[PDB]
Picture 1 (cartoon, each protein chain N blue to C red):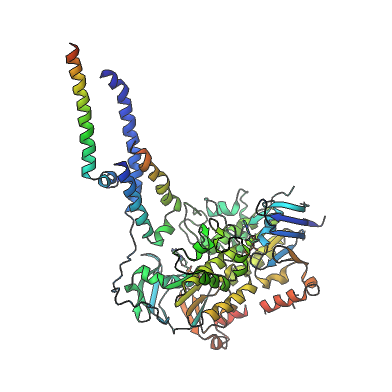
Picture 2: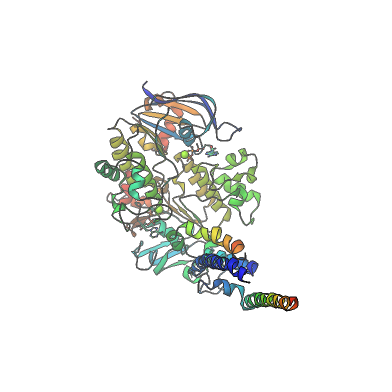
Length: 50
Length: 238
Length: 41
Length: 294
Ligand SMILES: Nc1ncnc2c1ncn2[C@@H]1O[C@H](COP(=O)(O)OP(=O)(O)OP(=O)(O)O)[C@@H](O)[C@H]1O
Ligand SMILES: Nc1ncnc2c1ncn2[C@@H]1O[C@H](COP(=O)(O)OP(=O)(O)O)[C@@H](O)[C@H]1O
Ligand SMILES: [Mg+2]
Ligand SMILES: [Mg+2]
């Protein structure tokens, strides 16, 4: 279960980010977008299945 | 003595054990005057500016400061903005002094910009704040450099992101008026040769070395080719 | 919604298999301890 | 089992609080997951698009008014122009006059709430975004470099040979600089291009656009970080190398577009003057003459 959700959520997030308009990238800070890949994805891959 | 910075035979390298990006650097920057560093792309201008500051490793030569360097007001070529507001970026850990703040705002012509944004002069800038235009980032960095009470100002291409009117007003009201009245050392790296008549001192760079260092009357006789080349670029350079 | 994204990404089959297998394992352990209590008497 | 209550009641409460925090992380990822996407589908059929839909480079702009978001001021107001194929269009104006949004309008990076941009008989709003943005080249004022080789920065999809990369570097005045590096085309560009100067980074982005070899080039204040001496020879070699290609050059320096075929003067998002520079400089009261004189 941990492997399946860890693969699928990162694939969906990476595909949905690159299609979002540049208005979204200018309005939202890059730290808020990047911390989902950095910290939240690290929790989903490692901390949640434990 | 009468100079601010001086380098004798300076060999400086970005890499720890590589080819020297600067070779035979010999500069005599006067104090209280405007020194302009001019040259082509990748010829050592920002490297010279950071070699005086000690940011680049020195292989040989000597660097003398007669200002123990002390503070230097620096505006980098890529503008650096803190996560704080417009006012905190311009002040940059300094007492407020609203009479000087209005003069710096009018010299950079940032007054129409603070008449927009949701909280003018208080909007958060940079990351976690509103995004600015590149010219606005450049002018806020230059406003930070001009605002401080530092004897030495280092400007590294402040007119790259600006048009003719903003650069002319920043040159006249900011450099020739706000900085000259304080008797401030100004070292101005620029690609705009039309401001060469406003320069007290000129340092010409070519492939990481000092090609010629002197006034415009010196360049009229010592380097005839570069003087006529400058005249062809901007269409008797007094 | 946003809190239920993990359950939807896991799927019904995998999540139900996890819950059922954990419940069955713990009730098997309870049965082992009860049979040990009956055996020791 | 009572000893297990004493050991595991605390562990159950601790794991419940931990699971709430983990679900907060999943909640943040799902909140970023529901962000809207651009419409990459396109109304026009892919068979209706030719293999080279910029066949010659004609650009028609009909009543174009663009903005960046709904309930926002239109940065361009009633823009209407025609660009014959092979013509050079120099765009000048003060900062804030909407001349970079003009460049972004061809790539549908702005909200074209009214007006059309018809390129070679095809409205670009009908086209897919990858189809539109793959056949046009743009050079932004601010350089953007990525970590990797010079070959990766110029050609990330590896669709062009080394001779094309060397021609792109030679036009962008980087033949001697890249040849001086020991790797050559395999010389490593750092994160953000910190091992090169600002002008060299911008010339790398110019050479990155020269690889694509399209029909329409849009140089949005490309030579702002470049000294005038190399800017003039770069402008000359770009004009000679792209003689048959429509180039829309946004001028950081007005004297660079004195040799352009047509000059578009923008005042506050409106085209005040759109004519040849020879006739435009003949008028004493023209704003383009004030740009050249001052
Ligand atoms: N941080 C750095 N690390 C390594 N090499 C560098 C660095 N900065 C510059 N160089 C190299 O040193 C040389 C001088 O670059 P420098 O920073 O002095 O450019 P510049 O003259 O200010 O450029 P421009 O006028 O184009 O903005 C170039 O060949 C460049 O590749
Ligand atoms: N990313 C953006 N989001 C919202 N508005 C923008 C954005 N970029 C530019 N603008 C608006 O466009 C106007 C400037 O247009 P622009 O094309 O940047 O002019 P220039 O080409 O002279 O820099 C500004 O008033 C600004 O408010
Ligand atoms: Mg520099
Ligand atoms: Mg612009």
